[PDB]
Image (cartoon, rainbow, N blue to C red):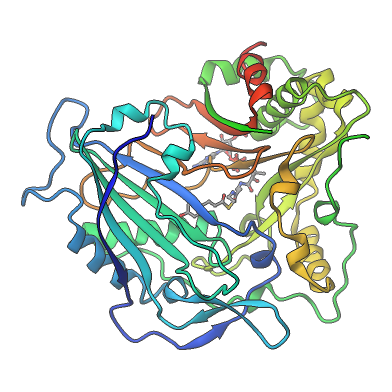
Length: 435
Ligand SMILES: CC(C)(COP(=O)(O)OP(=O)(O)OC[C@H]1O[C@@H](n2cnc3c(N)ncnc32)[C@H](O)[C@@H]1OP(=O)(O)O)[C@@H](O)C(=O)NCCC(=O)NCCSC(=O)/C=C/c1ccc(O)cc1
């Protein structure tokens, strides 16, 4: 259906104090992440478990003025967020820290309730909860951060975030949002951001020592409307799925990501009807912070995304989750300090990094992307009126792109949010539970 959603006011929000005016150099990983405003949506319920109103003692519940004041404070240490994209003399995209501000707006949905969104699948209707950005040829023209706070008939609220990917990855993006939340809640946030990105500069001279398959063009089909859905697997399902894989003494244990990813990859491949000899490539975003040595400063503010790309004939992936999980874990296992360091050097040698940008052509059939949010603090944004009951991607712009989401409660379930061709989704829906 098409929900009535009325925007009651838009406002640019600026840092509430002096911030540095500068150009901020972007690292190779900053430049190869997707070129969108990464969409996320938060839902907050007006009543708790037992039916108590979650409004504060002063009657507030996501009061706009308060949120904007806290936002302005947050933008002082996180000042690149209030910047704009630009290019350096060489044509390399950078951030112009010019305190141009972020878009904040409020909306009302007078006839819809949080419950109407059901499972919170990242449909184009869910995307309506994030402000829309008009992309022209002037890359400096739009804010890097847009936010909408939407109020519902039930008293509940959605916060829709869109964060231009050059500025921050998951950890750094949520570091900002959660810090904003902390300020709004009336507590100082624990970790000041570290802004300079030169720590991720390549070595001089660059000395790559791997082919870096992750930056090579993805396989094409050997010589359509995209559906979106979300699927929960209970702790017991994930257990049973793991128990299907032989775990023998002396064989290193597969990660839950590798097992689940093998399952998703196998199901998508079967649903797409891939022949056994069709190559297929799975794109796995990997956090460099856990891999680089010495570790980066705790508050490093930027992208530290490296990419693991298992690649196999569809025959290997569909033969079973055991075989697919092994291929994925091997690809993950490659992602150590020396590999991530080599990748920085490799990216430095490229004449034009915009060519390596991951987008529609990257994730589309016969390939796949599976971005884990399992260890991101997506449920910690408490602005003063409680923790969210759901957080997920606002939409999924590319076919073949999927997310692993952790549960908002303690049940240890995981959900897979995914986009596939409509004809293929109909099969995927059945296959993901058909084990
Ligand atoms: C993706 C990998 C390869 C797979 O891992 P994962 O699903 O994230 O899970 P982990 O494997 O790291 O952690 C799970 C394991 O760790 C264990 N564990 C688990 N939490 C614990 C614990 N607190 N204590 C101690 N043991 C534990 C847990 O038991 C579990 O064990 P096991 O079942 O044996 O696998 C992992 O290495 C990794 O790099 N994860 C991070 C990937 C990442 O950075 N994704 C974000 C990309 S950027 C993006 O999407 C941006 C979004 C965004 C969003 C909002 C914005 O505003 C802006 C942007």
